[PDB]
Length: 460
Ligand SMILES: CN1CCN(C(=O)Nc2ccc(F)cc2)CC1
Image (cartoon, rainbow, N blue to C red; front, side, top):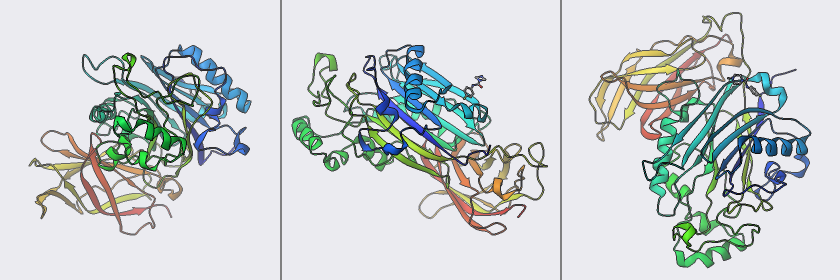
């Protein structure tokens, strides 16, 4: 039975509005409704992994697991295995997998982050799950961010707290936050970004939605504008939105948006918005293709509609050679040549690098680089040809060309990371000096760049 080189992943996000679901929710798992929808001919084909994020979820874990598993069984005739379930307050993530994947899945981690302080602590935050699928690390974050049209900056702060403090994946990757720990990271939820138009334009907005004319609304979507100004979700992707705003509906129909201020809303307007979103970030040159992104039309218990997204994701096998794991394979080497970091910092410490990769027995620390001034005010840290030659555990190009090297640049004075990035080993050539590049971030914000050349030796 061959190991897969591709899987499909279902991501669902639904703010349930503290109401039990209706008896049938199969349309959600089938990616049927509005937007980019799944072909009818696929309906019986199970996804490999289903990741369900809920917010304002009133059900027990048991109650929801029963509804989810019976739903999928009705669709596919497959009894899914529960990989993980984690709940913070009324924010929940469930991961289900086909039974054939049970002995492909390991290193299951769960965590949560509570956002805000005192007043603003006690209902918003995030839950997450990570695991290994054979040789591929997968991370999943379900976040319910701060509500309200005038709180986009709070949402951005919530995002940074979640990616700083959510403890998923390999704890040995100590300089790296969740935005660098996974081959594929999916981040979804009620992100609560709104369409930033005047309140007086509510009926105009509804008109546009009824005509399926989303362009002038999307140009005011706070998540798209904030992402374009690099305020949030730097280096994440989102499929094009081709479905109606998923909030705020009158319950038990989808024919009415309930946008007017009410005591129950704290006298806030809720103009129709795309609150409910799915974003991802995969390591460079790994296959990831969005195959659906849309909302259901027929699930109306909540003031939100469910959102679905599906993906093809490249995966690798758990590689064994005569040599590694358990030793290095002397036919393999990675050389980083003529590299330099360009940093936005004003600090005047020396810097060293750390190289982290599951193709190494353990992480590798460099010597200190040489600091110079850039022409436009910047710090440039030069490493020359001084960098340690990296010794991978397996030399086979079928393994090594699929790997990645995480880079941290750290202060000699404090050992703290000033920037993190990732380099793919999916090169155009081996035994050939080739340009490499990664932006560097810290707490998910741009802090600089790393560039240079690489020369990769494999057993071929
Ligand atoms: C800490 N433990 C280790 C064993 N364990 C597990 O193996 N779960 C699993 C479930 C479903 C699946 F598909 C694969 C693995 C539960 C957590």
